Image: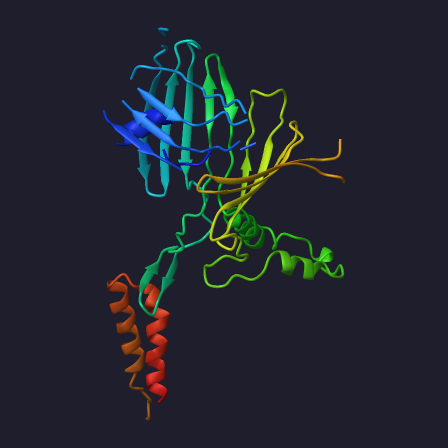
Length: 273
Length: 43
């Protein structure tokens, strides 16, 4: 719950009661009215509005569906497991969410003047390697939307740290004398300062919306920039779909969206506002 | 018959300092402490 990446059941479980909270190419208007079961949530944005109405009781089929949520967090990791059973489909769908599982590249430092350990206190927790695996019926690999919400500094710093400490020494000498190669190496991998990052990469993200349901391998790449410069917050996402042929420039801030679905000349972009 | 013998007190002090730091399971401080002691001898 409250993770990147139905909802009425989770809202009711959050707190056997009733809650109502208010706030897309057509607006998303993400508002949740939960009662448990009333599951009023606006979706299916295209005028002839259409809503996905489905009355359920908190396989028999209007059609009561059962959603079970198990939530347990340990340290930085936060685990959310969702099991949804729909009577009409007669197949159970799973959902997993893990937060901040990112591998660590920093190291503990002993201080002799204070005679004390100094753990990697840089614990900003911006790293978020979300893994969403959904299994539907027999098909265990129904969907794999593994898109990391980390600042990408975690990954780039881990790569450069692995290269610098363990690979540079084994590199042969004769390749170093190549002109401008040492400058390239220095620019790519700079010298470490204290235990901090070599490159300060923050705010960026790489959301891979892959799905094994689609034929072959057709992932969706969405680079998200989350900075306070853009109107005091709000994710500016550029998503390129390998099949839908839509480059989505989405400015999303607390449910307020400015979505421009841009299609390459069927060079000369075509813009959907 | 002059047989020289030297008064070795600083050597014994350094050895005792090493022993005391060893008994405290703080050998990593050794090179930090002993060196300072040597400087105290110089000035």
